[PDB]
Amino acid sequence: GIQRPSLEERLESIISGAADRRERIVAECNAVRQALQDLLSEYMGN
Amino acid sequence: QMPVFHTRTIESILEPVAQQISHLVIMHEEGEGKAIPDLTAPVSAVQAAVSNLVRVGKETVQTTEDQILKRDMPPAFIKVENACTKLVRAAQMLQADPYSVPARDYLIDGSRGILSGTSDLLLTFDEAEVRKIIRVCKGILEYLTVAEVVETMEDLVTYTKNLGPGMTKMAKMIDERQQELTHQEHRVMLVNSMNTVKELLPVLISAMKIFVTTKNEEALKNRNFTVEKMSAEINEIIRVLQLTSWD
View 1 (tube, rainbow over the protein chains, first blue to last red):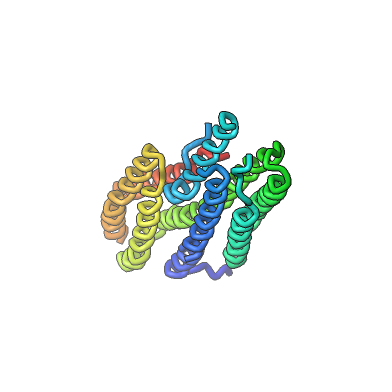
View 2: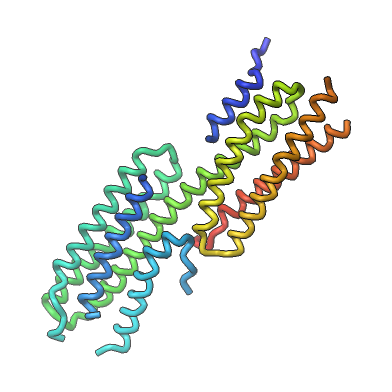
C-alpha cells in the first residue's frame, strides 16, 4: 500500500518548496552611471 | 517615448543617464573644434566600470538556482560590452580628427547601448526578485488547498502554526515590493488585495474551528468559500506583480 504523508509531513514539504547581492549590483550600476556621466560631461562641458 | 522606469531604485540609477543622453542629442543637433579634450582616459573609466559590472553580475548569477536568470542575463552583458567598443573607437577617432562625424554617432550610440544594456540587466534581476515572491504566493495557494483535510482541533493547531508565519512573510514581501513601484495604480491594487487576504485569515480559522468541532454542513461551505476568495486574491496579486511596461 501507499505510505501517504501525514499532515505535518505534507505541510513541511509545501513550506520547503516555497519559503546583499542586490546591493552589490546597484553599486556597480551606479559606478557605471557615474563613469558614463563623467564621460559625457567632459565631452559636452557640460 | 521611453516609458517610466519600473522601480524607484532603477529610476534613480538610469534616469540621469537617459536625461543626459537626450541633452547630448539636442546639443549634437543644435550645437556647433579644438575645445574637445582627450576622451581616452574617461572612456577607459567607463570600460573599467562596465567590466566590473559584468564580473559581479556573473558571480551573482553563479550562485543562484534561477535557470531563467542564467539564460536572460548574458545578452545584457553583451550589450554593454559592445557599446564600450564604440566609445573606445570614438575616442580614437576624435583624437585623430576633432571634427569626426562617425565618432559623434558612436558616442551617442555607445552611450545609448550602455543605458539599454544596464536597463536590461536591472530588469532581469528585478524579474528574478518577482519570481521569488510569486513562489511564496503559490506556496500559500497550495497551503490553502490542504485546509480541506483538517478534521481535528489538534490538526487545526498544526495547520495554524505554519499558515500564520507564511502569511506574514508574504505580506512583508508584497509591502516592500509595492512601495518600490513607480506606478500608483499597481501599488493600491497590491495593498488592497493583500489586505483582503489578511482579514480573511481569522475568518478561515474560525470556520475551521466550528467545522472541526461539528465533525467530531454550513461550516463546510463557508470554509471552501473562504479558500476560494483568498485564492482568487493571491492569483490577482501574482498577475499585478508581473505587470510591466518594459517588453
